[PDB]
Amino acid sequence: TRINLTLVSELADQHLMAEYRELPRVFGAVRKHVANGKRVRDFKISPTFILGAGHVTFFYDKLEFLRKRQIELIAECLKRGFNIKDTTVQDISDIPQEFRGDYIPHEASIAISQARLDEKIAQRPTWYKYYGKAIYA
DNA sequence: CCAGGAGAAGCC
DNA sequence: GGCCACCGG
Image (cartoon, rainbow, N blue to C red; front, side):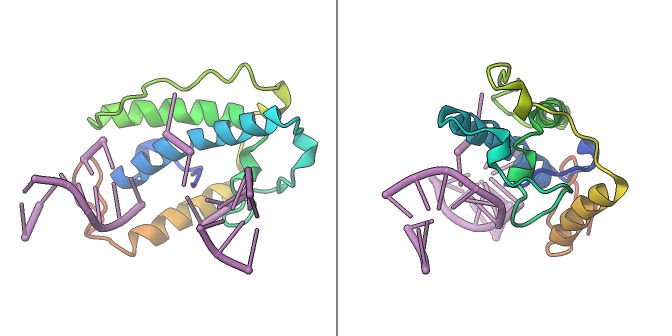
């Protein structure tokens, strides 16, 4: 389960599909927490973007950022011809406003996210694809 | 013919 | 201390 901060249109086919199906898991995790009376203050939430421990929790108070990114992930999936079923983001207006903040990453955060993507591609450079082509080979 | 392959954190 | 919205021989 990984949220990327990079340009959705730059994502490799396999990374695009992954984030498309994984990002909505955060809405569910938070809703279940609100169900148990949890509040934003009851979570760690790193002050800066991180991968590894704290990664998913980092977005628990940034659902508006996620909602907007899922709209782009969806549009990109359709642009490339993916036969996805869920073409809309779930409504999140039922979730407390406090969990729905926007977010503007700094260049370093965006670069840390990109480095992870690049590290994964370097492991199978002839296999990842972009619009169906092995452009990383 | 349909399986491989794109980890943090909630729960016992 | 462990056990969650798709695209080729």
